[PDB]
Length: 62
Ligand SMILES: [Zn+2]
Ligand SMILES: [Zn+2]
Image 1 (cartoon, rainbow, N blue to C red):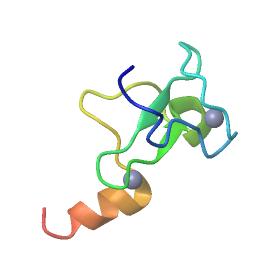
Image 2: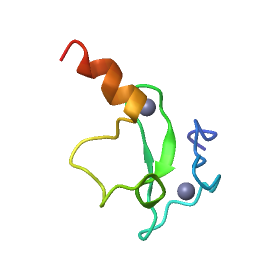
Image 3: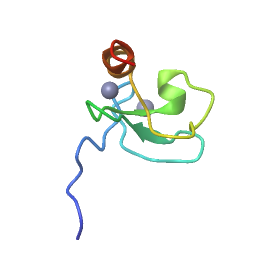
């Protein structure tokens, strides 16, 4: 075994199933998990994911 889950469940649909059509992306700060299709994102980005609270947090200092 490796890990238990660490927020391995989507919030928009409460489904922790990482699939091609709906990949449950993990944040970078808070560690929120949500399918890129569930949140409303075109697809998987280059780096990680930053929720509106996440990006807004780091956006301050920049
Ligand atoms: Zn979802
Ligand atoms: Zn976040």
